[PDB]
Length: 168
Image (cartoon, rainbow, N blue to C red):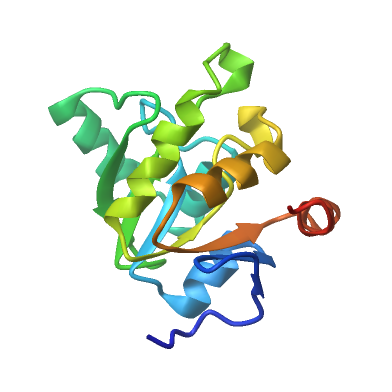
């Protein structure tokens, strides 16, 4: 079905990419699902998580603290579905491995598998940015793991250009 995502470059049958601020993208599109680059404690301090949470006026963090108090931490590679607040219907909080914590990069595939539970997503590259993985690798794992339709927002123009120009 046609959708309102605009200005994306088509990488594959199901994966699309754009140089964009995921906060502004979500505000404009109001997708069914926005993906957060979460950690196991749902402490949304920085990176994508800090930015999404700030855009919700801290409502994402309040909701997340109640989630953790009830359910305990997520697993690396795991996820939970919470409200999308003012950004989306739902937020899929996905924990990619954090290389700066020594976590095993193989868990990146498991992390992306969560996307297959949703027909359409707006997402960042998992484990990129402050999570320390190579974004070119993250894009490769995304393409090779996600089968549903995923619209990737890449914050940095230089990185976006490198991701497109090196894509096999």
